[PDB]
Amino acid sequence: SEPQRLFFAIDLPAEIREQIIHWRAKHFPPEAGRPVAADNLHLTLAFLGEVSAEKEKALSLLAGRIRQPGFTLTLDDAGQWLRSRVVWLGMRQPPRGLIQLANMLRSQAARPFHPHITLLRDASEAVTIPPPGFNWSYAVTEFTLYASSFARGRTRYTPLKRWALTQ
Image 1 (spheres, rainbow, N blue to C red):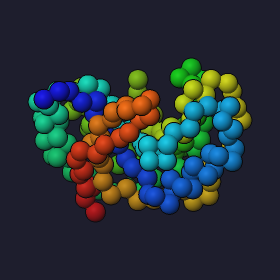
Image 2 (image 1 turned 180 degrees about the vertical axis):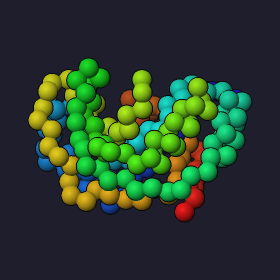
Image 3 (image 1 turned 120 degrees about the vertical axis):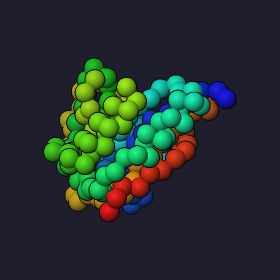
Image 4 (image 1 turned 90 degrees about the horizontal axis):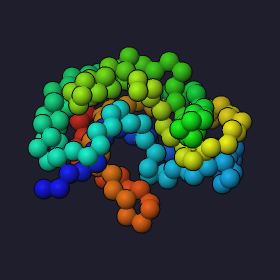
């Protein structure tokens, strides 16, 4: 029927989301920027924007043809992009499995890919950016197709399809 705002993403284990939002509430005041909800924390592999039902279906097939071993993400980096006004969490040297998976999703769907997890939005002022917490590392077993929707000015992500990575 009606188009949906879709995107692919890598998710976070529950315990690490909790570890992150605690680390964020320690080094960043409300004045620092707008905090991303715990359940909204993710690593976007490919943003699709408004997609028709026909286009979504074709993408889900192309996504299902992907064959890739799982990989490990260790979040050793955190930073700030001043123009886009975001405080992000990421990885210094991302695994080849991450770069490959993203590029394939960007290729099938089609700014260079710089994998990150947004922690704060509207972070217009510069702020000292501490390093991430210790041992924020986990195994990636799957990637998910998501559809976003904005109810009361609050963002909610709804999962549509999940694909496991070989392992």
